[PDB]
Length: 117
RNA sequence: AUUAAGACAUUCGUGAGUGAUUUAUUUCCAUGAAGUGGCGU
Image (cartoon, rainbow, N blue to C red; front, side, top):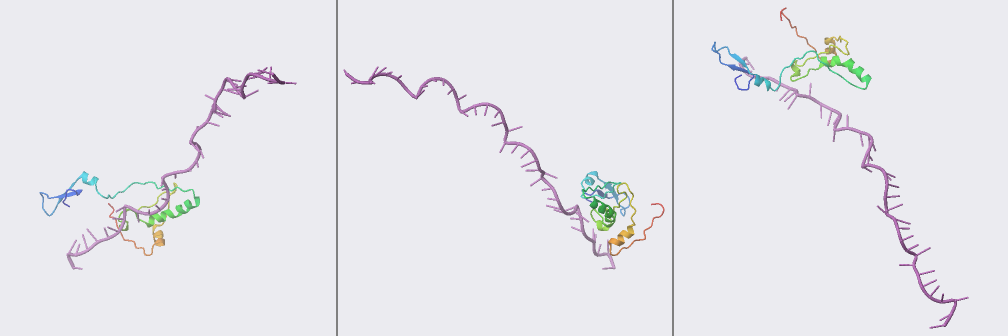
């Protein structure tokens, strides 16, 4: 918008007024309340002196990460994570089967990619 | 003038020597910085 605190400061342009330019300020971006972040592959460690609980957790962890979203506005798709390796073993979980198992209604959208994106 | 008289149970002597109020005990357990758009029909 137009204020001294906005990270993207929209300013009048010498071009056609119907189009507006933008300015990026690092100080405002450094003090924003929340940021959308994407990381590379990272580690979740679970420690327990109960071995049977660890086995049960290994059984249920992929389903848990397939069922719940994390972060702010997690209803709308932010913070989606899936399990790739468990104890240096790849995990093969049918996402649709897990979603069907743990949810009442499931719907899938016909998304498309035009061979370039 | 009498089987009598005379005579400090007294001198010396440190209640003292060696001795950590110490061994042991997690200021812990629980918990989503998160909920939500609306008009422009």
